[PDB]
Image (cartoon, rainbow over all chains, first blue to last red; front, side):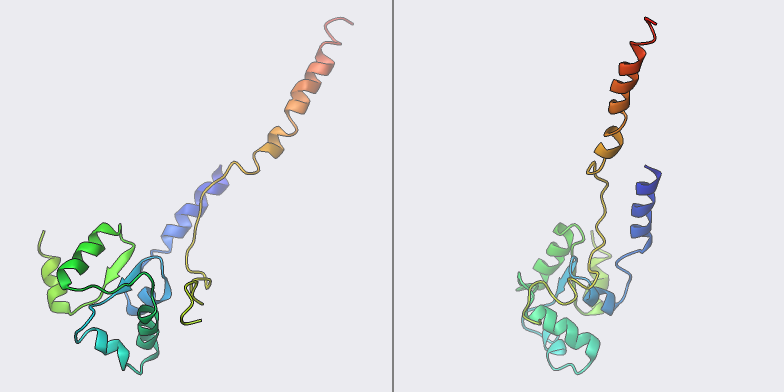
Length: 101
Length: 49
C-alpha cells in the first residue's frame, strides 16, 4: 500500500505540461492545432526551425483534424476537451479570452 | 513515421500511466488460507490430545 501511493505523487510532481512550445510538441495526449487559413497556419508551413517544423509535420498529419474553421470554435474546444487539447493563436486574442468569462 | 498515427514520439515516453491493481493480490492469500486451513488441520488435534 505504501509502495503504490508514492508512484502517483511523483507522476504529477513532474508537473506536465510545463509552459513552452516544445513541451506542447513532445506529448500527444493533449493535442494542439491552429486555424485552417491564416497567418498562423502558414507560419509553420515554411518554418525552417526544428522545433516548429516538428509541430507542422504533426498537425499537417494529425488525425483527427486539430484545425478549426473559425476562432470561436477553437476556444470552445479547449474548454470541452478536459485539458486534452490546446490552441495556438496570436497573443492579443489569447489575452482577451482569458479576461472574459 | 511522419504519417504514422502511433508517432515516433507516441512511444518515446509520451504518457506516464499509473493505477494500482489487484493483479497479484492472490500470492499473499495464496499462502495464508493454506495456513488457516493448516492451523485448522493442526488445531483440531490439540483440543483432543
